Every structure is written in C-alpha cells, then in structure tokens.
Image (cartoon, rainbow over all chains, first blue to last red; front, top):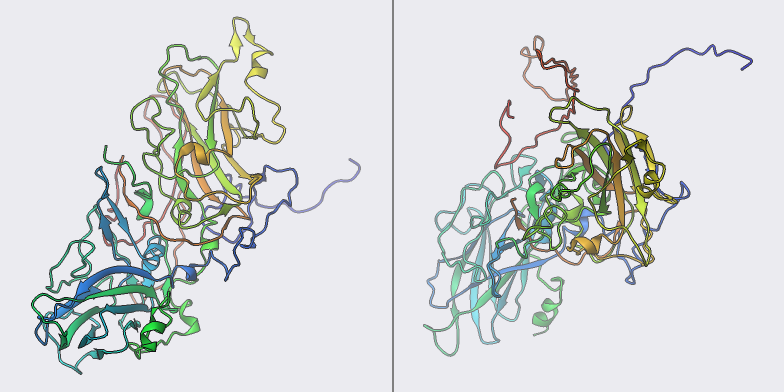
Length: 278
Length: 270
Length: 54
C-alpha cells in the first residue's frame, strides 16, 4: 500500500439482470464446468449423415416441399368452370380429428408456414406444383390465372390478367412460381383464434370440403389469388358420367422468401396434442 | 413417356418451368430502408431470452408435517424447457389426475421437434420475488444453483423438497450438512439482499452423441437435471410465498442436426 | 411535439427513461417489487389494448 491512486473516477450503471434482447454482445455468466474454454463441435457430421449445409439456417425451411390436398376434374364439366382457388400466403392450415378411438384435434403447416409463425412480416415468392394423375389415354387442357389484388369473383378473360394454358398429353407435373406483386414492401402473417381455422383454399378432398365457390377478403395477409379453370373438356375412352381424375398440388418457398420481425402469437400453442380433451 | 418419368422424381426436379409471374428485383440496401437488420439465420435468433415457467413450491404444503421456521426449499428441474401442455408426468399437479406443465411455448420448444438430434448447452436466468402476506417482511436469504450428476444409486429425485435447519437451541451443525452436499461440480452462490438474479450455463455431459428433440415425457428429458434452492426465514409450512422467474436461451454450442419434418400442434389452454 | 407537426414524414427510434416512485399512505411501506418493459408487436387478431389492466 505504498503509492496512492490519482486516476479520475467513472460511472458504473450496475445492470444487475443483464441484456435479454440482443444476440451479439458478450454475456457475464458463470459456466458450470471445470475450464472456461470447454466447447463441443458444430460439425453436423457427428450424427452419421453428410451435411448439405447449415441445417439451422432458415433457408432449409423455405425450400422443403409438401403435399397439401387434391381436387377433381370430373370430365362432365363445362368449358369454363372453377376447379381450384387459393390465397398466396404461407399460412395454410390442415385440421384432422384422430382417426383412432378417442377425441383429439390437431393442425399442420408446410415447412414455409411453420417457420414464419414466430415472425410478423413476410415477403418474397412462392412456388406451386400441380400433378395430374391420369392414364396414357386422357386428353384435356387447363388454365391457371393469377389476380394481384381483389379476387376473381367471375370468370376472367384470357389476356386481361396473367394466364397459362397447359395440356394433358405425354407430360404432367407442371410447376410455377409467383413473385411479389404488391405496392407495399411487406405483408402480415395470418393467425388463428380458435382450434378450427377458417377455410383458406377451396375443395380439398383430405379435409372433407367440396365447395367450388370462390372465397376471398384476405387482402392484408396474402399476395394475390390463384385459380384453375377448364379450357378444353377432359376426354376419356370409356365414357363419361362416372369418370373423374385427381390433381395433387405442392407448396414451397422461392429463394427470394423473407421474414423480418419478432412475434409472440405462438406463446400458448403446444406440440403435445396427444391427450388434451379428457 | 420419357417426359412423364423424369417428372416423377422426388423434390419436383423434373417439373416444367413456366415463365414465372413477374420478376425478382430487390436491392441490397433494402434492410437500411426497413427494419434495420436481417433475420435469415435461426442460430442467431435462438440466442435471445424468453420467459418460461415461473418456478414455485406449492406441492409439499399438503402433508401436515412440513417444517417451518427457517427451512430450506429445494426444486429439481430438467435442463430443457419440457414443452407446454398435459405431459404424461407433469411437475405442476402430480398428485391429481391429468398432471400438466403450466409453462409457455418458447423459441426453443417450437423449432426443436422438427429435428433428429440435439446437443449443446443451455443458459438460464432466475429472478427472485416473494412476500409474506402479513407477518411483516423478512430478509431475502441465500440462493444456490448446483448440478446433479449421474449416479447408478441414490440420485436426487425431481423437485419440491423441504428440509429443516433448527432445533430447540437454534442452529444445528448436523442438520446443516444433511441439507447440502459436496457440490463438487455444482454450486454458484450469492446473497439475495444485494444480488437477486442468478446467471448460469449448464454443459451437455451426455456420454452419448445426442438426444431426441422429439421427447415429450417429463422424466425422459429429465436425464440431465439441476437444482435451485433458497434459504429463507420465518416461513409457513402450508403456504407458498417464494418463487423464481426463469428465462431460457441457447448456449454457445447448441446444435440441431437433421431437419426431418414439421410436427402437428394445437391451441392449449389451462 | 413542438418541432414535429411542421413536417410531412417521420421515421426513427425513440428513447425513454422511467423512474419509479410510490408510497402506501399508511400500512407501513412494502418492498418496491419488480418492473418490466416489453414491446407489443402487430398481430391481426387478439392484440393488447391500450393501458391500465390489473
């Protein structure tokens, strides 16, 4: 204790509890190990499978395809009839009812829909793929229409809006991607207030819904509307009045998908749906 | 027919591109226009803290022999948030049909079940609060957090034990040792009168390469556990007057390996 | 609130400082307690209203 300190004083700001919001600053915590440098690997290869990249990146969710539902063609169909109608947004629910013996409910989302729940704003493109299940002797032609805003309450023209005509020949399994066509930079994310969400797309055979009328009024969360119309009637060798054909569709996220927010809407949901009715 | 076979491989790599709707035109300086920063990485996102499952001790107030008068209250809990709902075991209502876990779904119990493997450390923050409901307030006391290692015999059970400390002539050096242990790899100690919060990080120490992030049973996730205990005076044996607030984040080596699929979910209320 | 209405656009962050005080008017003073400040994000359904719930 020979000398004396002649340095100027300073200010402290105790900060008893610390910073619980940022994710880039160091932390003053007490590691309960022997050394302060203990550390495992982040290899992704120690489980037994070669890694295609960082599996904790959000891009791995935007890009995983998923089968949603099916709709019919019903060859006894006029030249302009609505077959499919959906909203272009990733939050598309699917509700089931526990086939086995008990009463239980649940919901499902695509990989794109699942990852945007903890967020509040979304933007980017989405990819759709339609596959027709027919034999080698089926002929027909279909139409795909996109409406940026307002919905399609009536059959549109052929060039007023974006249209595509595809034919059922020796090739099936067509895919198409919708980009961002809004006047705003970001849109909102859909939520649900109860356990039975409202319909987001028209007939899906898995969910027992078969209404062909066009639903709408979801402008504040979606990026337009997709519709499917007949162009040339389906032709089969045997004979109509009893013959149909099923089309399966898949959803995905384009490489330009984006989310930027933080939300607390999933704070009271749970992945344990097994026994919650009693 | 070649065009119908190539378009049937998994992933839709044989589908026909169809001249997409519009064009993609995004500038690099869009983050400087909206929201300031980007949210493209989930590993960075999971390093923030989330409120979860305030910890109480309202399960031992039933038997008419619980000690009072400066006793020790101890709770043993798993190392993982143990997802919300009516889990099979349940820490919140065990001696009553259909026990449940009165918690909230955090950012760790939402992105985890979509995976095959899980390994890494977890960070916790415990904040103390409590009153006396009359019998004018007493000092806070002492708080400790220590690990519970694996042992083939005589391991500590999960949660809510109370131990006495005093006798007719005051403190006893013998009972003060039966309510503690060696703490050879555990305790961080503090005084709650000058510091009410506890920050701790708990390593993996698994002896296995990983664990199942789809686990749901409370005891299955409770293979790696720790304990939070507090020493307080002038307590009541039939009331719960102290609690902790738990905030959970991800450690520096938290990992999730293989994205399998998205599981179902529902709206749960208690 | 004096220099702002003379403008067309407004954007940016705001900084706040909250200082706590309070008594009991008899019933001799209790400990202060715990205080929290948190954001309320935008949600189409079930958003928090403005103020004064117990």
